[PDB]
Image (cartoon, rainbow, N blue to C red):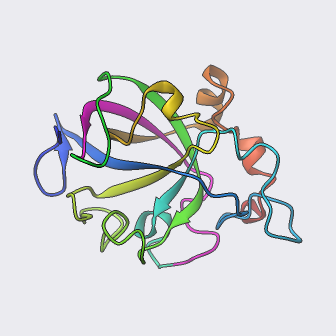
Amino acid sequence: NQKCSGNPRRYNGKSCASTTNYHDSHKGACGCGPASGDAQFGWNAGSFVAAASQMYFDSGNKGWCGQHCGQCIKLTTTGGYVPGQGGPVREGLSKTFMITNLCPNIYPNQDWCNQGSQYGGHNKYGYELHLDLENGRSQVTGMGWNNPETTWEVVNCDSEHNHDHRTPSNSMYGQCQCAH
């Protein structure tokens, strides 16, 4: 059930983000792997990392080294989820994800990553931001997070890395080609 309401979707005065658990093993759109090739670094697969919907990744529509590459986003569960596209979770759980990739506004993401603007737009379920969360090692579903509805905020990566090492540090993002 969606607990966020309005256009775009909000919850008690906070902007909401939808999520989808996904797996992608390619280097990705922030260059977070060795320069020559299409592989990731060793840390990406087991970290709290995300692909951001296109207009948030970069409002100028870039597919490489977007504005928000390397930014950390703290997600807090509302307790809700999109019917038939997620499941129940305790309200108030929170983890921080580093943006390392793009969720492009093209098939098969046309229902989720199709916001028309960086802020104030909506996907087909009403959310102004969407994050695909890396889950190939069950880092997200292991917490009982099945595509939770969330509220979101920007935070310092280092502060959150201290509480959970799976959130990459700023030093780690410095390895990525887009940091330079």
Q: Is residue 67 above or below residue 131?
A: below
Q: Is residue 117 above or below residue 6?
A: below
Answer with the quarter of the image where residue 43 lies.
top right
Q: Is residue 79 left or right of residue 176?
A: left
Q: Which quadrant does the N terminus fall into?
A: top left
Q: Residue at x 43, y 27 (%)?
A: 144
Picture coordinates of residue 104 (x, y %)? 47, 72
Please tell me whether residue 125 belongs to the stretch shown in magenta: no
Q: Residue at x 27, y 64 (%)?
A: 123
Q: Please give the range of residues in magenta.
A: 62-82
Answer with the quarter of the image where residue 157 lies.
top right
Picture coordinates of residue 166 (x, y %)? 66, 32
Q: Is residue 54 left or right of residue 13?
A: right
Q: Is residue 31 above or below residue 137?
A: below
Q: Residue at x 47, y 79 (%)?
A: 60
Q: Is residue 91 left or right of residue 99?
A: left
**Farthest right residue?**
36
